[PDB]
Amino acid sequence: SVIKPEMKMRYYMDGSVNGHEFTIEGEGTGRPYEGHQEMTLRVTMAKGGPMPFAFDLVSHVHRPFTKYPEEIPDYFKQAFPEGLSWERSLEFEDGGSASVSAHISLRGNTFYHKSKFTGVNFPADGPIMQNQSVDWEPSTEKITASDGVLKGDVTMYLKLEGGGNHKCQFKTTYKAAKKILKMPGSHYISHRLVRKTEGNITELVEDAVAHS
Image (cartoon, rainbow, N blue to C red; front, top):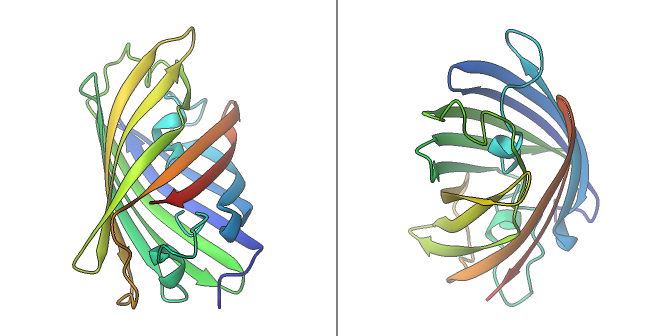
């Protein structure tokens, strides 16, 4: 098996939100069978200076890192060595929205994760553009299968500075590069994604566990 108990990650993203272009590059380490990742990510604005949005907007942008019980087929680890891609729509409760897609490849014990992100129609005084969210709440995503691909649906909430919630619906399609021999049936993935940010540098930790 090509998925080892310790693995490494390299990340690159081309993105833009409300017209502001940026890149993100970073790296981490993780334990795929424990469903744990931790990484450091660095944002660079094309015009320079501090990023003019909350990092939660892109933090959710690596399913091999999910603890799967033996009794649920693990599509994401089965997708390797050949590769795994995914696509996601975000719809925020204030009319902001975004589309992102990523391709994940593997060389040696290192995953290379390459993404393109476009975010539009965020209110200038809303919590994403004003950097007022601080994390996502933990969530449970429902995973369903059809025709060799998976779909995930999860109602997410930003935690706001000083206490509110702000809703975002995620709809994701997950696509193995090569046809998967053992497809799972419908199930859930429990996530806890937590960030600690200093300006344009963010440390992120995710813990994810599948269950039926």
